[PDB]
Image: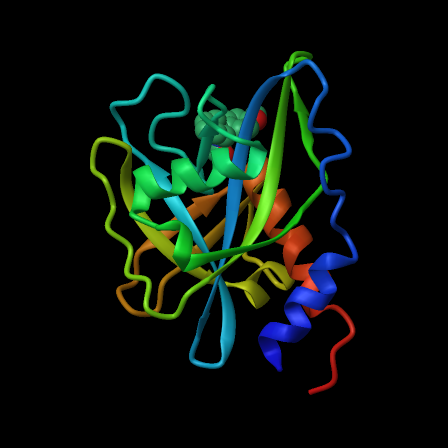
Length: 186
Ligand SMILES: *CC(=O)N1CCC=CC[C@H]1c1ccc(OC)cc1
């Protein structure tokens, strides 16, 4: 099936806990895969304008590890719940992708999660200004704008709203698209 095939692909790139003990400032993100109309989508947030770090920016759900978290995956799930109302029974964490090194002292660990079909996002306005889906296939043929570095523009056909996706977030979206969609029969 589509979902079984995505999970089997993703598992081949799972690094697991290999990098998880290293003495970094630790953040985790959840790459939430949602199946709609027979195709996979990624769920993104727009961060609230009010926040200290990264205001107004398009990010996957996530944030800084805290002492309650059992592990790095727990961080990602906690932050997803606070930001968009995603409960742990509504997500299957499939794998841990390559971590991202930032600022010499920070390690960001991405986890890919399969999202239950009955999940309905409840944006928390203290954390997130918007939540939106992009079809995974988009990241194979994105609409690129050079601001000099590359920015993706995605226009939702439901309402014509354009979103700008860039940086680590854009890079991770492309990675997941390649993993799941490369070399597939039609
Ligand atoms: C957009 C995003 O995922 N994050 C991670 C967790 C919450 C705020 C920081 C933000 C971020 C990650 C990576 C970079 O690299 C330049 C910048 C912001």
